[PDB]
Amino acid sequence: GSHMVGQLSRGAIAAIMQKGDTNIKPILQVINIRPITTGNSPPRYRLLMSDGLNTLSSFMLATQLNPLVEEEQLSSNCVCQIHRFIVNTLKDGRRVVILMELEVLKSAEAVGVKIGNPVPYNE
Ligand SMILES: O=C(O)c1ccc(-c2ccc(F)c(Cl)c2)o1
Ligand SMILES: O=C(O)c1ccc(-c2ccc(F)c(Cl)c2)o1
Image (cartoon, rainbow, N blue to C red):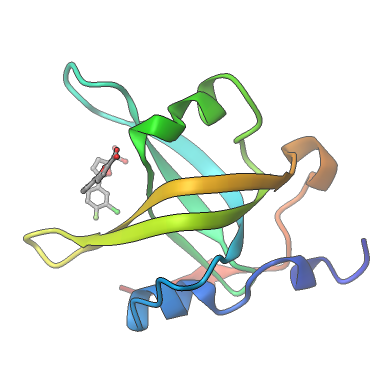
């Protein structure tokens, strides 16, 4: 699959954070996933995602999507299409992007590397 960066929705991260563009269904790569410290509740997963241009670590999976991480694909390097998300703003001004529906387009094993050379998005 030549031109790998062409597989990702370059600019979607900026669109999500500067426009609050929500009527997009961007294709992103998972760079990393880690659990967040939660007390008793179901675990919550934070994701570092890439659009080919930028990475952003403010993504959180909706708890209903937990089985994707625990049982199925969802792991570093996979390529996913985000079908539903919402942005939430914390009292301190930071924004978190909650992933509500997503589809794994390519498994981690089928991609195998971080696509392109994305740099961290600022703010
Ligand atoms: O253990 C962690 O990784 C963790 C705990 C809490 C947060 C967090 C809180 C507010 C935010 F906006 C973002 Cl991006 C992250 O990350
Ligand atoms: O369905 C869910 O699991 C859900 C809906 C909204 C949130 C949420 C809202 C603010 C946050 F900071 C974090 Cl981490 C999550 O999680």
